[PDB]
Image (cartoon, coloured by chain):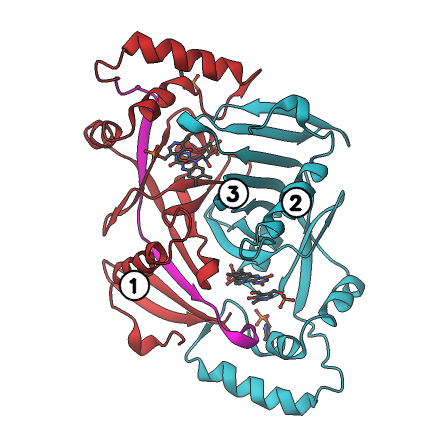
Chain colours: A red, B cyan
Amino acid sequence: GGLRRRDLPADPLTLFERWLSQACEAKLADPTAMVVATVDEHGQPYQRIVLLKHYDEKGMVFYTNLGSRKAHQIENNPRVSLLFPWHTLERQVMVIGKAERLSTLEVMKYFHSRPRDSQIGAWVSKQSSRISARGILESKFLELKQKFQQGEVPLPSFWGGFRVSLEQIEFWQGGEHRLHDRFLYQRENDAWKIDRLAP
Amino acid sequence: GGLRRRDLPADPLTLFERWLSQACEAKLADPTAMVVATVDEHGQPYQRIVLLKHYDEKGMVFYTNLGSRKAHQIENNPRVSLLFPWHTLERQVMVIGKAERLSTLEVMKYFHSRPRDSQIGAWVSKQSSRISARGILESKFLELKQKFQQGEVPLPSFWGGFRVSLEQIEFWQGGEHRLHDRFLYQRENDAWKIDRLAP
Ligand SMILES: Cc1cc2nc3c(=O)[nH]c(=O)nc-3n(C[C@H](O)[C@H](O)[C@H](O)COP(=O)(O)O)c2cc1C
Ligand SMILES: Cc1cc2nc3c(=O)[nH]c(=O)nc-3n(C[C@H](O)[C@H](O)[C@H](O)COP(=O)(O)O)c2cc1C
Ligand SMILES: Cc1ncc(COP(=O)(O)O)c(C=O)c1O
Ligand SMILES: Cc1ncc(COP(=O)(O)O)c(C=O)c1O
Ligand SMILES: Cc1ncc(COP(=O)(O)O)c(C=O)c1O
Ligand SMILES: Cc1ncc(COP(=O)(O)O)c(C=O)c1O
């Protein structure tokens, strides 16, 4: 139908929820999958996909290994971008914001909700580091599977999460003749300013 | 089946071609769609999706408006990342490289291959700038549609392209227990060094 300004909610999260909901409703693969880009110390951007696990006015949350590249990069530069690749629905959602570490309480809560085998997996992988063979991973997995026996499988100290603040949220929706609809929500003192951007 | 080092081609492009081919073969939406991330002058990364239009040992090519945000950003920092979001196939391809402008000859060649209405659209949109209403776009479109009458519709001077060099190419493929396969191809003097990365 198109995207007209007069139909936009004041809070970008309202619009995001609808699009997310419809994405699940359309059974797209991993509707919560978002591309998170970070920057290293030399000005070089880096990307990898992560899963959005929670969101609210404070920002969007995802979990990762604290010794990974994305983590090292965020510690040197917290500015990150998030892009939800919903093009099968002719849609795109981009977020600009600052990443901050979640508290152990939050992390513990979420970690103990993941499939056991997944919790064990968390222990196995020294994310982003070069390993000489896949076998290293599989061996540790088995070793830990029984070591724990799963008394409850502990939260690794190198596992955490980040919350990305909402400073800017862009919505994109397909248009014919290459003339798409773009609306940029810009935080401006707890309030949002909306502008249509040329496609 | 999995991804073992012994099965990797020496040239990462060989592996990329197979995965791209299979992606089209699987009828994923826009198999050529890739997320391109750039960095602004403040260290802030930015993302938007663009279409890969050509690739070879020199790098990956895509077209865009030369006055856009991505273009301004590339002019200040040419380091870019490219991520092909093929997660419906439990796959991921990430490229690190430098973006460089294509020559007018190349651009002219590709531009005149796009649907007429698409060529006209190129003229209409001052990409990334704030516009007060969608009507601005539609009006110009009609005005230009007949202005040109389409004698051939000229190449706008503000339309171009970039080629991103292949300095690093990462392949990711789903694994159970969160233990995925990751291989990072690293340019090292016209040659490629391969390392498996912890997931
Ligand atoms: C659909 C999908 C979901 C993923 N979710 C996560 C996630 O939530 N956290 C994570 O650390 N890695 C996740 N990954 C793997 C990452 O893309 C990446 O390989 C890993 O975090 C290491 O990135 P880094 O080396 O840039 O730090 C996911 C991959 C796919 C394809
Ligand atoms: C599937 C798909 C393909 C796209 N391909 C391109 C492209 O090749 N070139 C382009 O300039 N914009 C393309 N866009 C629109 C961009 O994502 C973006 O909105 C536009 O280039 C402006 O980005 P910028 O403001 O960061 O410069 C595409 C969008 C989608 C969803
Ligand atoms: C390395 C890694 N960590 C975390 C996740 C997702 O978190 P969870 O296992 O709690 O669904 C993924 C999903 O693919 C992943 O690959
Ligand atoms: C699975 C895993 N990841 C990360 C680390 C430590 O991270 P780093 O060596 O980058 O300080 C460890 C240390 O034992 C680990 O076992
Ligand atoms: C603004 C813009 N430019 C270019 C393209 C793709 O190039 P082409 O029209 O030659 O297929 C797209 C595709 O969605 C686009 O949205
Ligand atoms: C469609 C379009 N894009 C871009 C520009 C110029 O770009 P900028 O104002 O950022 O120098 C023009 C100038 O006429 C234009 O017509």
Q: Could you confirm whether marks 2 and 3 are on the same chain?
A: yes
Whole-percent x, y for residue A10 in the image: 24, 67
Q: Residue at x 39, y 52 (%)?
A: A96
Would you place residue B19 above or below residue B116 in this image? above
- For disc 1, the chain is A
Q: Secondary structure at mark 1?
A: helix
Magenta region: which residues? Answer: A154-178
The picture places residue B56, in percent across and down from the top left corner, at: 75, 46
Front-lying residue, B104 or A132: A132
Compared across the picture, whether B192 is left or right of B30 comes to right
Establish whether labels 3 and 1 are both on one chain.
no
Residue type, label 2: Lys
Q: Work out whether A73 lies above or below B26.
A: above
Tell me, for residue B98, which label it has, or none: 2
Where does the N terminus of chain B fall, quadrant-wise?
top right
Type of amino acid at the residue the image marks with label 1: Leu
To which residue does mark 1 refer? Answer: A15
Q: Chain of mark 3?
A: B
Q: Which residue is mark 3?
A: B89
